[PDB]
Image (cartoon, rainbow, N blue to C red):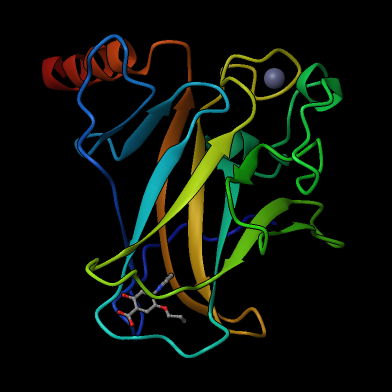
Length: 197
Ligand SMILES: CCCOc1cc(C(=O)O)c(O)c(I)c1-n1cccc1
Ligand SMILES: [Zn+2]
């Protein structure tokens, strides 16, 4: 099986937002709207905004899951490579096999699906802080796209789903991710490739 990636705002008008970090050599996380693609360094903070048009009910949650973007790999579970799963960099909550972690939220829950074996991380929805119009989740990606025996240079998508208390779908959005040493340079390169095409 393969999780759906269809964008779905749903009844609450759910969608993602990203900061405008630029493409300087020093940038650690940067989002390309033209590519719908996040470029980030290993284990660095990736701020992802959640936006809604109306308030979802108490108990609504936000889940993140990675899948391979290419159809011929979509049924393979995205996991950390044989090196990183053994490097003992745990935060005490994320299983060492999980690619995606949530940073700084003790209510994050990590799921190994008993039927699909896919990994995901889910947090309770919290309303924006006073003076803010959206809520931000801080994600970390714990392997490079190039890691041998893991992603092995294959592109991935992150699927973000808004779910009710039973796990039923309320909204969905997604973005491609490249985890790399120089996200600013790679974003510039890929945007230029797109322009040349
Ligand atoms: C279910 C708890 C409340 O959830 C929200 C409420 C509001 C609001 O304006 O009332 C909001 O703007 C957002 I963004 C969320 N939200 C947090 C994560 C996903 C959606
Ligand atoms: Zn790795």
